Image 1 (cartoon, rainbow, N blue to C red):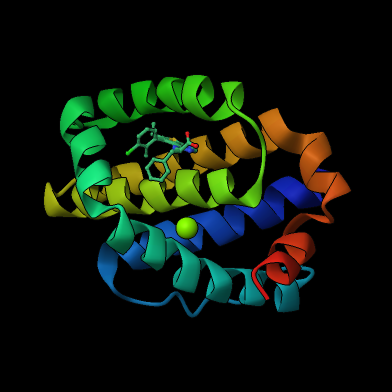
Image 2 (image 1 turned 180 degrees about the vertical axis):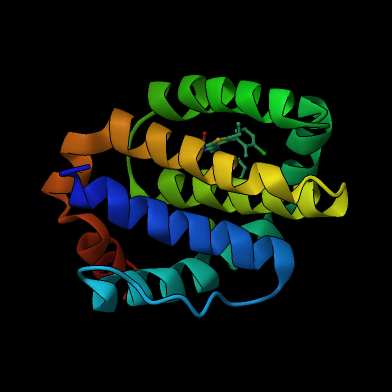
Length: 151
Ligand SMILES: CCc1sc2ncnc(N[C@H](Cc3ccccc3)C(=O)O)c2c1-c1cccc(Cl)c1C
Ligand SMILES: [Mg+2]
């Protein structure tokens, strides 16, 4: 892991999904550019919470269709995310939608007592994001670009 973008992405996305599922903020320290990661996480909270509230019926509809019951079902979610996310256009709107839906699924995992699947889902979403949109993210200045875009 000589890959700061992946590490920083995994930290932000893992922390968001964990706090959304449990309702508790994580007090573990951030790594390297914590100042950016902290601002990105605060942005994700405002915009990601907005997406889940505004599009609740759509998210509930997709969740019902995916019938998530365990680690096996979370693994096939990953494959749907590459098809849906990777085959469409790239912008922070779609990236926030992917992560927001991750957080929605994370709350479901906590509701069905499968908390152990939240960290793997976060890894899977981070993999989709950084593996498929690497050059776009670097061109946009990564999570610094994310913070700046949402003011
Ligand atoms: C597999 C679920 C995913 S992953 C993903 N990543 C990026 N964008 C997505 N959907 C938007 C359309 C949309 C925006 C807001 C709310 C609902 C849909 C896109 O493709 O541009 C999606 C959807 C996805 C795709 C279709 C429906 C639903 Cl509910 C989701 C969560
Ligand atoms: Mg919007």
